[PDB]
Structures are given as structure tokens and as C-alpha cells.
Amino acid sequence: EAPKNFGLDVKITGESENDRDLGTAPGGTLNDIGIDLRPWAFGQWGDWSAYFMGQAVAATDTIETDTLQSDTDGREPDKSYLAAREFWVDYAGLTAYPGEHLRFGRQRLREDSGQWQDTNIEALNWSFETTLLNAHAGVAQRFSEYRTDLDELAPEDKDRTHVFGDISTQWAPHHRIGVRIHHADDSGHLRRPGEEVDNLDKTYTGQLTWLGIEATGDAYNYRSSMPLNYWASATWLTGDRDNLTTTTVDDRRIATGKQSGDVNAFGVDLGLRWNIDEQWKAGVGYARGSGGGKDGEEQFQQTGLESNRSNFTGTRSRVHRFGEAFRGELSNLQAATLFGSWQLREDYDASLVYHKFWRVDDDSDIGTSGINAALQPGEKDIGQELDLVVTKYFSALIRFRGGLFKPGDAYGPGTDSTMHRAFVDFIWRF
Ligand SMILES: CCCCCCC/C=C\CCCCCC(=O)OC[C@@H](O)CO
Ligand SMILES: CCCCCCC/C=C\CCCCCC(=O)OC[C@@H](O)CO
Ligand SMILES: CCCCCCC/C=C\CCCCCC(=O)OC[C@@H](O)CO
Ligand SMILES: CCCCCCC/C=C\CCCCCC(=O)OC[C@H](O)CO
Ligand SMILES: CCCCCCC/C=C\CCCCCC(=O)OC[C@H](O)CO
Ligand SMILES: CCCCCCC/C=C\CCCCCC(=O)OC[C@H](O)CO
Ligand SMILES: CCCCCCCCCCCC[N+](C)(C)[O-]
Ligand SMILES: CCCCCCCCCCCC[N+](C)(C)[O-]
Ligand SMILES: CCCCCCCCCCCC[N+](C)(C)[O-]
Ligand SMILES: CCCCCCCCCCCC[N+](C)(C)[O-]
Ligand SMILES: [Ca+2]
Ligand code: NA
Ligand code: NA
């Protein structure tokens, strides 16, 4: 029971993916296995503490062993690599509240929805968590991937600074109301007209502010004592973007200029979960990120730090809010969701999730997704998905996570009728 100074997490993962581009491009499917080793070190001395976690990965192909991985020349991952995941120092002595502390270094930033921040990033982050009042404030920026195989940052991350904060209160037992803010500022520059544009150039620079209000009733508490749980959130995105314009000239992309415009967009996510008994749960969700509008002003996007993974099905396992296969970003996207889940004590859980997805504006792209295929102008029907997650907890666990995506009319002729992405993870902690 003495404070544990080190450990090692060992994960074996298999991934089957077919076909991310729906058959539109060559190869690019996965059926592969890998091991991921994460040694960690922790020290604590009165109000001070410090932590390091590293990572070594070897796999048969470039599979996803980390749900929080950076998305990917200079950005080509290798089948095997080393990385530094977290390295930070923490000071808890500003106040006597044990849930209050200040953390500096590359660290896990997470809030419960996963929709604003859920990532490892260099940050200075203040947390204040007590029974009646929670608050946080921080700043973050990526300076490197800290990986042996990736030499450059993604253009969206380069020179982008994040500032954010939140504050919330438990106004009745198990019911929380709060506000949340995030601001992203780009100090980079766009290619100038006539310059060649490649995959490591920015497509835009922005100064963007998200302002959100969030109500939850054990939304993400898998151990809730209430028969009904819920989440409701509404988020306003404002600010501006300078968008790069380009043209094609001889199989090469050339910058032609740029266009600025204000953003005035809106996102909402609602959910209701029935705690039917000690084991069974089921629920419904609706979410929408606005799209299109006059000069793209209504195109909602997320912060870029989000995972969209959360305990929304009411289990210990986190699930992708917009599908393991589709992996939607809330951006010109409407989603309806139904789920059921089962758990037995701390020993097993399982969730079955259905989604239907539509575009909001049928002449605009959606944001990120786990699908790499062009949408047909004028078609709103993105598709449907069924997901299954099943876990046995032995510390250690073994989990199946799978999604089956059925493309709708927005994907069109010559695309596959079905696509899946599935994982098995076996994890042991020493
Ligand atoms: C701004 C980034 C800060 C990065 C700090 C990285 C911290 C690295 C490793 C965490 C553990 C350091 C422990 C150092 C140490 O000698 O601890 C004494 C320990 O043996 C018993 O308490
Ligand atoms: C230990 C506690 C210290 C608190 C330090 C102060 C933290 C400051 C701000 C936290 C809230 C995030 C700020 C969001 C923001 O400033 O941008 C909005 C603005 O750009 C709209 O145009
Ligand atoms: C209770 C039913 C579970 C619902 C399905 C959730 C599991 C998701 C994926 C399982 C792997 C299926 C892989 C084969 C398949 O169905 O599609 C073939 C297609 O991907 C060819 O491109
Ligand atoms: C308390 C002192 C000990 C600190 C822990 C040392 C652990 C060993 C390595 C930490 C990770 C340093 C990696 C830095 C790095 O990868 O450089 C990134 C490049 O600049 C690429 O942009
Ligand atoms: C502009 C009108 C917006 C009205 C929104 C009202 C939302 C009402 C109910 C949604 C769920 C609220 C739960 C409140 C609740 O259960 O707490 C009451 C206390 O537990 C009393 O013991
Ligand atoms: C397919 C590869 C392995 C991935 C699967 C990991 C989870 C495996 C099995 C979980 C089984 C879920 C049902 C458990 C059940 O019905 O009751 C458990 C018993 O009551 C306790 O022994
Ligand atoms: C024990 C559970 C068995 C079901 C696991 C499903 C994993 C997906 C493998 C499907 C591969 C088929 N194909 C040809 C589409 O790649
Ligand atoms: C059931 C869903 C998880 C898929 C597991 C993926 C298969 C792992 C082992 C087969 C791949 C190894 N190999 C030989 C193709 O490199
Ligand atoms: C198992 C822990 C390993 C920790 C060290 C990993 C950091 C190495 C990063 C080197 C980056 C080299 N690069 C990308 C500039 O070519
Ligand atoms: C599609 C999922 C939507 C929510 C499911 C609703 C669950 C209602 C369960 C009623 C069962 C009443 N019972 C069995 C406890 O006496
Ligand atoms: Ca392909
Ligand atoms: Na403290
Ligand atoms: Na629950």
C-alpha cells in the first residue's frame, strides 16, 4: 500500500480494418497484430509529484494501439517505434483541497464527454475538483510527437495554442450544471500564391472560441444509483478562419490565395439512459453539429483535442460516441443513436450501439472520420453503424471493440456496401 513508484502496462492488440476507403483506392486494409509496452515512473513528496510514461511498439503493420494517437512524408508512421507519452511535474500545495493541483508537462487532458479534450499534450493545467464545485483552467500546445517515426507535427497542430477553462456545480445530488470555454489560436501562416502546396501545409489558420453549457445527471457514471441518467449540452462556436485556396496544375497543387470569414456555428448533444436494473441499461442519443451556411460560417468543428470517447453507454468501458468504424467528428453531422448495455459487477461489460448519420448541409464536407471516401454532392444519407464492445476484467482485461458501417447514398457508385473496423486488446498491468 506504500505509494507505487513504477509499473509496466503490456498490451497485445489485433486490428482488422476493411476497407477505410470503401474500395475506392488500392490496398490500405488491415489484418495485423502488435505489442505495445508502456513503462511508467511516479514519485510523490509532500505537495510535489512527477510522472513519466513511455511507449514501445512493434507490429506487423501500422495498426492503432493507442486510441489517442496522432492521425496520420515526415508523417509516415513505422510498424515499430518508441515514444514518450507523458512527462510532468505536479504541485498540489496552492490550497488544502486534495482535488486541487497544478500540472505542468506533457499530460493527459480529459473531460468526461471526451468532446472537448481527451489527449496527451504539453500543457499547464489547473484542476479544482470538490463535491460542490469543479473548475479547471489551462493552456496547451503541441511542439513534437515525441515519437521515433514521426518527424513533423500535423499542420493543424503546428503553432496552434489552446486555452481553456470550465466551472460547474452539483446543484442537486448527482445533477451537475456547468459552463465551458475553449480557444484555439493559430500563429502559423498559409502558403503564398504560386507556392506548391503539400500534405504538411495548413489548409487554414483560425482564431476560434467554443462556449458551452452542459447539464448532466450521472451522464458518465457507470455506477449510478439513479434509474435515469442524462446529458445535454449546447456549444456555440465563434471566431474566424483564413482558408487557403488552391488550384491543380500538372498533378501538383498550387496556392491561389485565401479567404477569411467569421464562424458562427452551433453544436448539441443529448442523451438519456435507462438503468433498468443492476446489470441492464439502454438509451438514446441525438447530436448535431451545424454545417454550411453563408460562406461556410455555420460549419461547426471540434477543438482538435477531442477523442469523442466516453462512458455514455453506462459501462466501465469507454465507447466512441460516433462509432468505432465511422468515428465521426461533430461537424456538419446529425446522428441518432440507440444502445443497450450489460455489466456484471466489476467483472464484465458489453454494449451494442446503433447509429444513423446524416449530413446537415449536403454541399459541404463533414469533418474528420474513419472513412476516407468522397461524398456525393446533394446527398445527406451518410449511413448507419452497429458497434459491439465486450470486455472481461480479470487490472488486466481483454476487450473486443468492433464497428460495422453501412455507407448510405452519400458515398455512391463503386463503393463497398459494408466496411468494418475491429480490435481485440489484451492488457496486463505490472
Ligand atoms: C516540465 C516537464 C517535467 C518532466 C518531469 C519528468 C519526471 C520524470 C520521471 C518521473 C519520476 C521522477 C522521480 C525522480 C526521483 O529521483 O524520485 C525519487 C524516487 O526514487 C523516490 O521518491
Ligand atoms: C490557479 C488558477 C489560476 C487561473 C488563471 C487564469 C486562467 C485564465 C483563463 C481560463 C479560461 C480560458 C480562457 C478562454 C479565453 O481567454 O479566450 C476567449 C476569447 O479569446 C474570446 O475571444
Ligand atoms: C450482435 C451483432 C454485432 C454487430 C457488429 C459489430 C461488430 C463489428 C464488426 C465485426 C467484424 C465483421 C467483419 C466482416 C464484415 O462484417 O464485413 C465485411 C466487409 O468489411 C468487407 O469490406
Ligand atoms: C527528471 C529527469 C529525467 C527526465 C526523463 C527522461 C526520459 C527520457 C526521455 C524523455 C523524452 C524526451 C524526448 C524528446 C524528443 O523526443 O524530441 C522531439 C524532437 O524535438 C522532435 O520534434
Ligand atoms: C427553457 C426551458 C428548458 C427546460 C429544461 C428542463 C429540464 C428538466 C428536466 C431534465 C432532467 C432534470 C433533472 C432534475 C432532477 O432530477 O433533480 C431534481 C432533484 O433531484 C429533486 O430531488
Ligand atoms: C473474441 C476475442 C476475445 C474478446 C472477448 C472478451 C470478452 C470475453 C467474454 C465475455 C463474455 C460475456 C458474457 C459473460 C456472462 O454471460 O456471465 C459471466 C459469468 O456469470 C461469470 O463467470
Ligand atoms: C470470435 C468473434 C469472431 C468475429 C470477429 C470479427 C472480426 C472481423 C474479421 C472479418 C474479416 C473479413 N473480411 C474479409 C471482411 O476482412
Ligand atoms: C477479431 C478482430 C481483431 C482482428 C485480429 C487481427 C489478426 C491478428 C493476427 C493476424 C494478422 C497477422 N498477420 C500474419 C496477417 O501479419
Ligand atoms: C520507451 C521510452 C522511449 C522514450 C524516448 C522516445 C523519444 C524519442 C523521440 C526522437 C525523435 C526523433 N525525430 C522524430 C526527431 O527523428
Ligand atoms: C432502445 C433503448 C431505449 C430505452 C429502453 C427502455 C427500457 C425500458 C425498460 C422497461 C422494463 C420495465 N421492467 C422490465 C424493469 O419492469
Ligand atoms: Ca482500399
Ligand atoms: Na491542493
Ligand atoms: Na449508468
Image (cartoon, grey):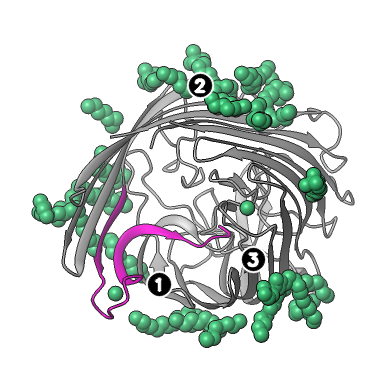
Q: Main secondary structure of the magenta part?
A: strand
Task: Determine the CA span between mark 2 and mark 3.
Answer: 40 Å
Give the mark, 2 or 1, whose residue is nearer the N terminus: 2
**Please, is residue 209 above or below residue 289 in the view?**
below
Q: Can residue 253 be seen in this view?
A: yes
Membership of 70 in magenta stretch: no
Please tell me the numbered disc located at residue 295: none
Which one is in front, 68 or 298?
68
193 or 354, which is in the foreground? 354
Q: Is residue 83 above or below residue 178?
A: above
Q: Do the residues labelled 3 and 1 touch (CB within 8 Å)?
A: no
Q: In this rendering, which labeled residue sits more in front, label 3 or label 1? A: 3
Q: Which residue is drawn at 85% across and 39% down?
A: 408
Q: Residue 217 carries which label?
A: 3
Structural distance between the alpha carbons of marks 2 and 1: 37 Å
User: For numbered disc 2, what is the local secondary structure?
Assistant: strand
Q: Mark 1 points at which residue?
A: 139
Residue sitting at 58 percent across and 72 percent down?
A: 173
Residue highlighted by disc 2? 32
Q: Residue 196 at x, y = what percent?
A: 55, 53
Say what secondary structure mark 1 lies in: strand
Place of residue 334 in the rendered image (x, y in percent of width and height, measured from the top left): 79, 56
Q: What stretch is highlighted in magenta?
A: 85-114
